[PDB]
Image (cartoon, rainbow, N blue to C red):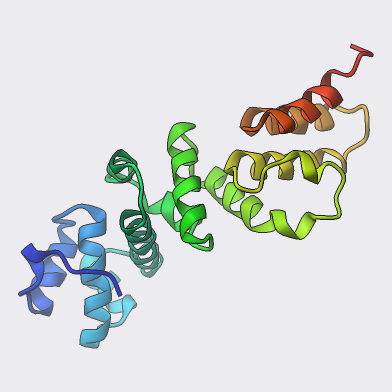
Length: 198
């Protein structure tokens, strides 16, 4: 599944389990030990019983580590990876459905703008959804390649579902503006939010 780190590759199950029970490494370093333990014939409930890693956290760690590994292999800035060393699992898990290229871009955006897990979920969902919205008003003003533009376009779509004028509409438009990256996307947002009634 993932690659087991050198320092751990000659452990029997018991050694892997004791390490996990002590969280005795970086999160993505003990994650492959979980995968490895699965194939030893150990199932998640009994791994939670022995280490305290809930079966949900297990999946999050394994999948996060694979996402991390995607970015690592792909050409990237080295500092990007360094940023996930602590609590990076919950953010990387959320972008797992994206392609490799999208993962590198989304992760970069998550780091630059300090996005939490919820926001990362929204971002990943927005990126994944964008191509399906071709017919929608304003779609051409947002760059699919740009994570913040994808998320911006989702907030903009949601704003067009609210009444105009309303505080809800205004709030969604201001959110769309907070994450927009391209000038074309900011142009449309400015045009529609600040339209010369104001």
